[PDB]
Length: 62
Ligand SMILES: Nc1ncnc2c1ncn2[C@@H]1O[C@H](COP(=O)(O)OP(=O)(O)O)[C@@H](O)[C@H]1O
Image 1 (cartoon, rainbow, N blue to C red):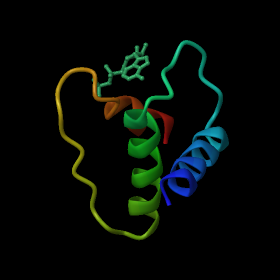
Image 2 (tube, protein in one colour):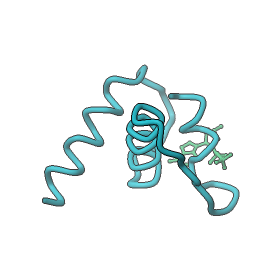
Image 3 (tube, helix red, strand yellow):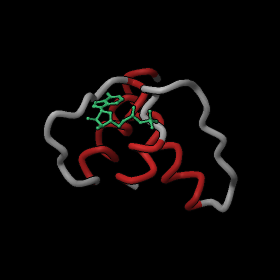
Image 4 (cartoon, rainbow, N blue to C red):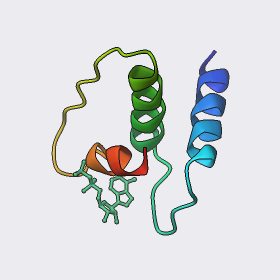
């Protein structure tokens, strides 16, 4: 299940334009994948954290 989830996250990140000098950590992948899904389904997303949690970056890439 974990492998399938990370595979879909990598797939969705691949769908987004390739960005150089950007980290493929679980943060960015999960953020972008879940915001794509949530705004697709009209369900709210509430990303939080601290400076460096790939939330605004995920917003811009989406
Ligand atoms: N894996 C990563 N996670 C967070 N920030 C990254 C990552 N890779 C690169 N960055 C840098 O972070 C900057 C914006 O991301 P970030 O500041 O983390 O967003 P947020 O506003 O959510 O903190 C970019 O200029 C980018 O160079």
